Amino acid sequence: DEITTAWPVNVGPLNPHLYTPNQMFAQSMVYEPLVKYQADGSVIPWLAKSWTHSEDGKTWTFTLRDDVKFSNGEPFDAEAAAENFRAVLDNRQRHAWLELANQIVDVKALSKTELQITLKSAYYPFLQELALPRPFRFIAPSQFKNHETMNGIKAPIGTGPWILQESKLNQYDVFVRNENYWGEKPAIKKITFNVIPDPTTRAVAFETGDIDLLYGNEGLLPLDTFARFSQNPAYHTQLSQPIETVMLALNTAKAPTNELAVREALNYAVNKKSLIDNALYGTQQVADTLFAPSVPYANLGLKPSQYDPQKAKALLEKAGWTLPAGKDIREKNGQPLRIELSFIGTDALSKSMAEIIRADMRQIGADVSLIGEEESSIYARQRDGRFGMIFHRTWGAPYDPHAFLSSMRVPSHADFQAQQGLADKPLIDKEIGEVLATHDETQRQALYRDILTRLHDEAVYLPISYISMMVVSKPELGNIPYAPIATEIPFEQIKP
Image (tube, rainbow, N blue to C red):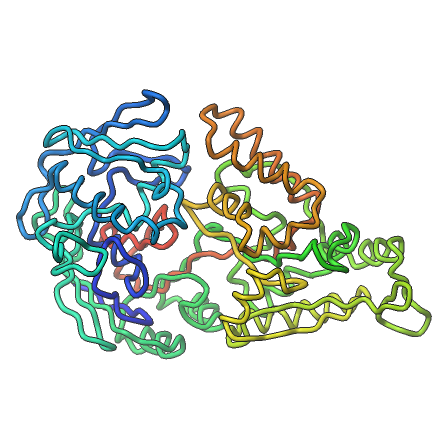
């Protein structure tokens, strides 16, 4: 049994150690990690069968399976593992975004079955970052070019359950089952991805039966089409639990968003449910908090700001943003309450949301300008702190919360810049450093509670909605599971 699906672009060459144009879901189909991420925020053995612990906190010895073969029959060895780590760290600077890349001090193969990795310091998200789709997974060293991968590989030969069989630029990628896989055999023997750039066209492909499956985030197919599919009993549709937050980041370094009372009022001003019914076709849940309570360490009981334009208006009045008789926009010492909202001008969902937000904020006295620009101009805006408000999102499992929070500490970025007006920013950054290094469960939770609580209570963000993974499927395919890792698709778990 066989399936046909769609993707906007080709899968890429599937170099397991590089980024764009390689597609993450496809790298995860073919290549495998030492240890596999779990929904709760923990890991299980995978290519490594077991491992040991702290010499200092920062040396680890993995005991590897001995029955695993690459898809060409060549053997998976700790030597092959060590070769992959070397090829990756040869290109260290490219993986700097990722603290493991920085952290790792040495990788040496002690024996065919034992592999030793040493760290700079005790970095609790170690295993979860080993478990990521890239870059720490394993290609046959025979496929290195001049003893490296950083400049390309020959054939994408992994140990995983799927093999990339055939590729055609802008047309398709075909994968086949690895009949020599070390674990459970997939029930599907072939998966063909038609390259279909346009979301409507993808929807039409599913309707006509040209494709069996769509599995994806909010850009997967038009959201009104999903809603309609979901009412049609010829179709199987599903929405996962929250996987990522969409929110505004508010610039606490620039008036007027530097006022706590202004951020509080903005947090009462948006009717999130109406925005979700109207713009998102009910595909997302209301977000009351930076992180969904189902995110590791974030089940904190933080109080939501309900939709309450009355409470907003009173805050602004009290902060000196007074509503003149006969006028709709408030003013403080002669200056109209204006706020600039920056978004990427070709992103339709972002544009539609931003229009809804302008109208809701006008009802509380704030005139919101909408500035839609090309992606690159928005990225500059983030780096520079040149914005009032901006759409923003968390990063998905397994990054949240530890990675999203780590990144706030970095001066060239939107969250570091937007947070410069917070009296306690240096304390929040220090506590983030601390949480990433801590080993005690309780202290870890205590610290995240503290970090997330300050960001809630200081109204740093305006959470809007949580994205759900969307599935549209032929019923014959049955129930479709969700991968713990947000960008993976569990093709290996589909049983018609």
